[PDB]
Image (cartoon, rainbow over all chains, first blue to last red; front, side):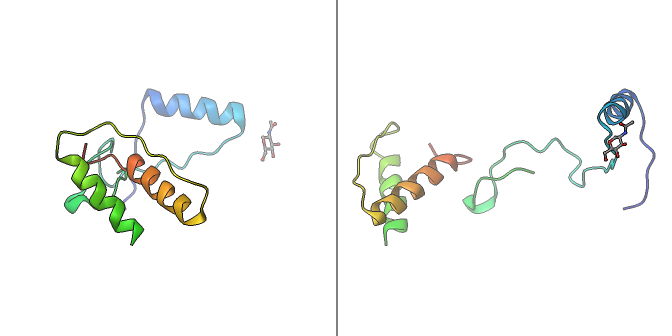
Length: 50
Length: 49
Ligand SMILES: *[C@@H]1O[C@H](CO)[C@@H](O)[C@H](O)[C@H]1NC(C)=O
């Protein structure tokens, strides 16, 4: 969990939303590195999301 | 038990080319657990029909 630097348009919109609604930013990268939609788990255990 | 019996019934329904189903029960507390299990299995649609 090394600290990376991420920026762009989405972070600017997030900062604007935080300033308008007095929020705070806790940006953290996803460990999976994917959107993580519905998928079939191994051995048909259960239905969950990643 | 009821929990595994519902799974067996659904596995049987998988064959015979059956996909649409509807169940009718009573107000007994034991039957409500079966209904809840069926609803959870329906919500568990990642695999199966
Ligand atoms: C923003 O909301 C926080 C709520 O924790 C409040 O303490 C703060 O005074 C607010 N700032 C403004 C400018 O309204």
